[PDB]
Structures are given as structure tokens and as C-alpha cells.
Length: 478
Ligand SMILES: *[C@@H]1O[C@H](CO)[C@@H](O)[C@H](O)[C@H]1NC(C)=O
Ligand SMILES: *[C@@H]1O[C@H](CO)[C@@H](O)[C@H](O)[C@H]1NC(C)=O
Ligand SMILES: *[C@@H]1O[C@H](CO)[C@@H](O)[C@H](O)[C@H]1NC(C)=O
Ligand SMILES: [Ca+2]
Ligand SMILES: [Ca+2]
Image 1: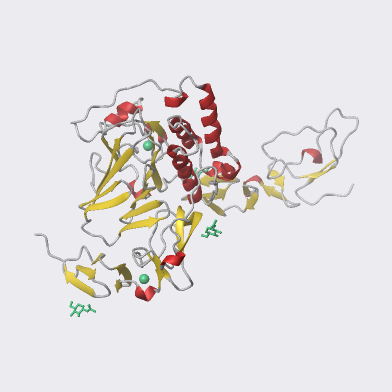
Image 2: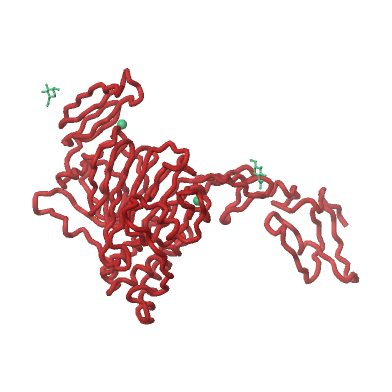
């Protein structure tokens, strides 16, 4: 019987003893909080009770590493998921609980998906506060309103109007175009980016809107606005179960009650409650169509979406897909079907799981129509499931802090060393853009850049005629 290296102690297995546990019940950094059942003990040397065997030596239990998705991380080695960091300390994952940047989203005709993940139905026909920071003791910087007309009982034909009020300006989203009714007092960080199917609005450093030009309206807030906003999109605090809090700080169990409390004009009437129809318009008493709609919308958890289903819950997009498609006479050309599915694929792509799902049979989209090679336009337009959203063009010469990584649609491809000119729909040399530069910032002709906004002695508003740059001092408002 040769001695064992400390602190391991030997275990002679007695055959004449009823039960015994040897090396078969060895405890490592993996199987510690588990139980063992030995057919017969294996004689050998094992670590003392307080320790576990790890890498052929006895280690303290607290010195055990943590495991994340199979990979081993030493104690102290942090992993970052989202905007939170998880430190490995004492064989445990200690994670921060910070609220990350969030997105409010209108899904489909009459559903809303709040910043904190609450999905509810609210078929209001008036104008409502989508998101605003005028809540109680308010700084009061921005207010975004949404008006729904035709998204009620007949949802086949519906149109929405979004009104954006920020920094003294009013930007309205309606009928697939952006209308800047009143400019922001400082346009330096204001951009209207048309990319693919979408229009991306930069409304300052921390407020953005992503819009598919029809009914998918998203507000992207940075986490500095947490607990500071209210309206149909909730209070943005990481707690989903309190987003149905009305304007009078009371939790409402019915979404129709919560939504009516955010009605803007007292002229129109509040929405009255209706019992939830599990089979709306064309699915009512039609088990055949309910099966067709369920099978079509079930693409959201099919193969191409399986990777994304782990990162982004498809349940709310699937509920909305089924509810809205039940208003279409045909699922092939159904607009509510493709838009809702595309809205999910868009969120997937923001999490690094770009999903190519369209086909010529199902929701086809091609760029062949606007590929005018033989017409004097030098630009090739190719569809991409997710291409960089904020590309440098003559109209956006400085690189932008884009609220989304990429978007779906048609994107122009230019020869090496050439930049897209959006107004001319053709590729041009970067020197040929009507673009000025000041303070290291390039801005397009007609854009106004404000230098030192808060400094009355150095505030300047710079204008770009074509390539001509002129700056003027600001006027003290008195
Ligand atoms: C994580 O660290 C904090 C201190 O930052 C401590 O209060 C908390 O108990 C730790 N949690 C775990 C599970 O180690
Ligand atoms: C889309 O663009 C990416 C780069 O942004 C490229 O790698 C990919 O091959 C493109 N796919 C299609 C179908 O154009
Ligand atoms: C630029 O503007 C100045 C006056 O501000 C004018 O004298 C000059 O001719 C302009 N140059 C061009 C190229 O337009
Ligand atoms: Ca909340
Ligand atoms: Ca620069």
C-alpha cells in the first residue's frame, strides 16, 4: 500500500462490506451538486471532503471555474451578455442587472410591444402617446404620437400617422414619406436615413425611430431614458408586468383601459372593451382557414428562424401574425403576413442572426424594377436580407451612429471608390457630392450644423450652399 500525495487519502474497497463508494463517486467542478449511485466502489485515492478533483489535483470548491455554453472561464474572467457583465466568482455567475437599450414597436394593426417586452392588443382609432418623457416630474424633451385610422374591425385597409416632437421640431411619418413640418432647433444630430425598406430617423444622440414605411414603427431608446418615459410603450424599467400603468400611475389589468388613458385629444371617444375573438374576421367559424393561417405563420419557428428563436422570442410575432392574417382573403399577397414576418427577421438580424426567408412564392421582393443600367443611371440594386443600415452617401457624408446594425431591402452597389448619390439614383465620385466640412464633420448641401450650441460666445450655425461653407453666429434669444 503506497501512500498517496497529500491531501488525497487512500480508499481500500472492502468486498465484505455491504456498500462503499470509491473513485466512481469522484466529485469534480462539474458534478459537485449531484448524486452518485455506484455498482461497486473503485479503489483509489480521493480528495478530502471540502475539495474536488480538478486537473488531476485537489482544489478548493470555490476555486472551481464557471461554465458558459460549454466553454470554461477562470474565476474572475467575465463574460458579457447584452449590456451586462457576468463575473465568475466562487463557482457562480454574478451578473449585473442593468437595463439595456430598448425598442418599442407597433406590431401589425393593433398590437404593441413595449420596451420591457409586454405585448398587448389595443385597437384604438384616435391619436395616442406612443412614447414620451413628459411623465410627472419631467425633463420633458420629446413626445412621439401615433394615430391609427382603419386598423379597427376592418384592418384590410389601414394607415398610421406618427408625429415626432423633439427639440422644438415636428417630424411627421405618414404615407410612406417623412415630412419635417418644423425643423429641430439643432439639426446637427438629426438625420433621415432611407435604407432598404426602412426609414431610420436619428432624433439626437439617444432617441431614434426605425420605420418600415407602412405599419412597423419602432422607437429605439438608450438606457439613459429608463424609468423616465411613459405612454403605450410602458415605463422602460425592465419590469414587464407593470407596463400597463395608466397616466395616473395606476396599474390597469385591461389593455383597453391602459390605452385609453393615453388618448391625446378628448374630442374622440374612448375605445370600449370587446371580448377577445380567438378566430377573428375570416377565421370565425372557419376551421379550415384557421389551420391555413396557423401553418403559414408557423414559419416563424421553422428552420431558417430556429437560430433566432433562442435570441428573440417569436411568440408575440406569431400571435400577431395569426391574428392579422385572419383578416386577409389570401395569405400569399397578405400584407399583414409579410410585414409581421419581416419585422421578426429584422429583430433577429439585430441579434446577429440574419434570416433569409423570402422566396418567389412567399413574400417575394426583388430590386429588378429599379436597376436602370441601360438608362444612364450607374447603380446596381441588389436585395439583401440585412445590409448595413447607415451607409455613407452624398446625402449622409459623415458616418453615423446608427440605432440598428443593418436593415432589409434594396441596397445600391457602386464601383470601387464611388459613393451613392441618393438624389440622382446613381454612383458618383465622392468629390462630386455637394458636401461641405466643418469641425471635422462632413454635412450635405442644405444641412445646418451647429457648433458649440450652449456657448453664446462661440455658437455658430454653418450652412452648405453647394460646396460653399458659410458660418454665422447664433442669435441670443433673450
Ligand atoms: C455579486 O457581487 C455583489 C457585489 O457587487 C454581491 O453583493 C452579491 O452577493 C454577489 N452575488 C453572487 C451570487 O456572488
Ligand atoms: C448581403 O450583404 C453581406 C454583406 O453586408 C454579404 O456578405 C452577403 O453575401 C449579401 N447577401 C446577399 C444575398 O446579397
Ligand atoms: C461662396 O460664397 C461667397 C459669399 O458668401 C461668394 O462670394 C462666393 O462666390 C461663393 N463661391 C461659390 C463657389 O459659390
Ligand atoms: Ca415596465
Ligand atoms: Ca470626420
